[PDB]
Length: 450
Ligand code: HEM
Ligand SMILES: O=C(O[C@H](Cn1ccnc1)c1ccc(F)cc1)c1cc(Cl)cc(Cl)c1
Image 1 (tube, rainbow, N blue to C red):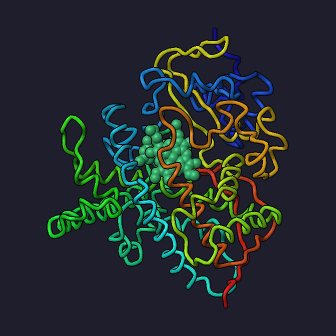
Image 2: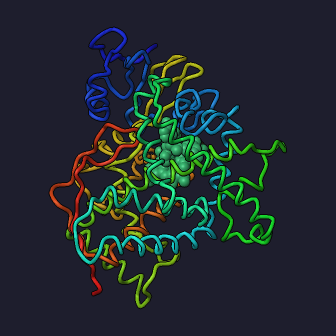
Image 3: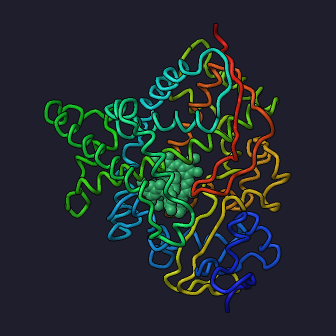
């Protein structure tokens, strides 16, 4: 019947301490001890970890009344908002809301986004000067905040960033959600709530402003390259004809931005760091750039679409250091897994971090080798060998945008600068919801064109 248990340190708390010490190592260690499927008590929750590629289809192809997302990620309600996303009234409503974000992520917008990336980096180079050292994680977070905001919200957001502290407000929301929220969703967090209200009022203002501009300039509606997520949200209704409330519009923008930022800034950090620290890798990347750029001096979309090796580097950083280390679902009915049955109420857990280091799937997995993908094709062994964007019904809809954003940023930065990373590549720090490199992450740079 039930899978093998990790014996608990204590009653209730169970395996929390070793889990909290390092959840990826926790799953590796215990998979060796107990197999492909084991269960653990963790601050009251029964958590069943699925750890081999071969068993993942049952997880990924379930429906939302078999394996529920809304039951596990509903603690995000104070960040994204009441009635939005995991706190939507239904699974169907949640799916429609996700479609509004995805509808500002079209090819047409992607061509405009490349120019945004060029513009923001040009502004950033003036702060950095011709030489120096900079924290990599912060540079990326700072660039991704301006770029993602303008990509999703339109250029009207830029004054609020540069003259109303919106970047700091985001960091206060990010500040007040920890992994413990998953276990205790009512842990009060008053600075987070203060910042969420502030961003709320700014986004309300942005919606009102946009309404005026849709009156005075209705042609924008026709032009697909100027239509951002704010615009769709103001002009689309739910499928059954119910109109959106501004509360929901606001929440959906906050959520989209939350997805738009942290995961990409972290991936960019890991990618850049490993690129510039491996001489061979850096040579191949620069040889592709020079071939694709030719005599042009700025990026455009079709150039970014030919950056295959740089794409493979990003993918390799996502194998090794996926920012979303664990994917979860609650069993609403018992579930068959292998010989076992997982019972109603257990949380199923799949980890892209664990998959990424599986010795089945990958050889020398602690080595950053983009050619493992580009030649040895190691990812395609199993159907679910690589899942840093998930799989199936709830696969990331931001994937192409993230690829575009991180390739572009790293390509532009390489065009401007020679860069050298200081010290050894860090380990992941398992202290936030979205997992990034352990500080410090510093690099030297110098401008290539005096
Ligand atoms: C490198 C950057 C990113 C990574 C690693 C990533 C990873 C993921 C993963 C693993 C999932 C599956 C979660 C699950 O099944 O429970 C997912 C879902 C999602 N991602 Fe991303 N993501 C990234 C960027 C983005 C961006 C830039 C956006 C939007 C701007 C976005 C929007 C979403 C949405 C809306 C879903 C939900 C899909 C659904 O449930 O239908 N993501 N992402
Ligand atoms: O930000 C979004 O999800 C991120 C995890 N994430 C980050 C990037 N891609 C996925 C997320 C999810 C659950 C958490 F508990 C914490 C963070 C998100 C999800 C949906 Cl369904 C809709 C929208 Cl608009 C945003």
